[PDB]
Length: 219
Ligand SMILES: *C(=N)C1(NC(=O)[C@@H]2C[C@@H](S(=O)(=O)c3ccccc3Cl)CN2C(=O)C2(c3ccc(Cl)cc3)CC2)CC1
Image 1 (cartoon, helix red, strand yellow):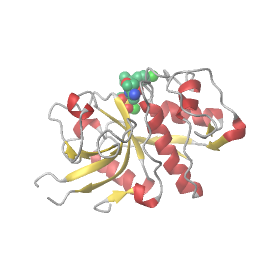
Image 2: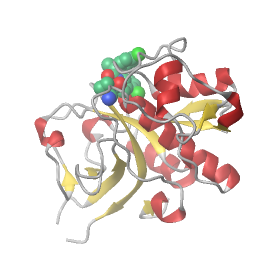
Image 3: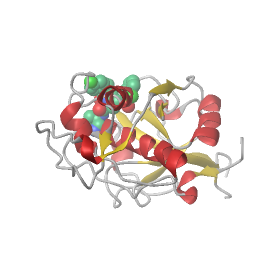
C-alpha cells in the first residue's frame, strides 16, 4: 500500500456534516462510504440522505436516532433498491415516517464487505477501495474535546465501540516517535477537531477499535 492515502484529494468525500442531537452517526458513516463508492462508479459526488436511512431502515434493525449499524444501512439500500439524495430528502435530526421516493434515488448497493479485523487489512482496504465505514470507541471526554494532531487515548477500547465514522485515508506526521494516523471524517460539524476530522493513532494496537468493525458497500 502507499505510505499515505487521502481520498478527499481525489474527489470521493463530501463536506463534513452535523448529525445534531440525533443518534444517527451510523447513517453518516454509511452515506460517507456509499458516497465514495458511487463516485468511483459514476464520477459524480452526490450528497446522500441520512434522513432516508434514519426514517426507513427499521426493518433491517436500525433504531433511528437511538443508534444503528452501517451494515444494516447498506442492507436497507440493497433491499429498498435505492437511496435518495440529501437535496430531495433533507436531514431533520429527528426520526420521522419514511418518505423514500424512488424518483429521487441517486445511489444503490449490491451488498457489503466486512474487512478482516486488523489494521493491516484496513490499510489495504482504504488503499484500494476508497473511504471505509468504521466503528470506534468515542466514549472518552478526550474525544469530545479533541482539537488537533494525532488522537491517542490510553483508555480507549479495541472491543467496545460506540460511534460510527469514516476513514478517508491514512498517513504520517513529519515531526516524533509515533507519527502514523488514520484520517477520520466525523459527523459533529466542522467546529469539532480539525475541520470536523480527527487524525487517529494508526498501528498502535488497533487503537479505539478502528479495525474491529470496518466495512463498505459494493455497488
Ligand atoms: C451514533 N450517533 C451513536 N452510535 C451508534 O449508533 C453506534 C454505531 C455502531 S458502531 O460503529 O459503534 C459498532 C459497534 C460494534 C460493532 C459494529 C459497529 Cl458498526 C453501533 N452503535 C451503537 O451505539 C450500538 C448499537 C448497535 C446496533 C443498534 Cl441497532 C443500535 C446501537 C451499541 C452498539 C448512537 C450514538
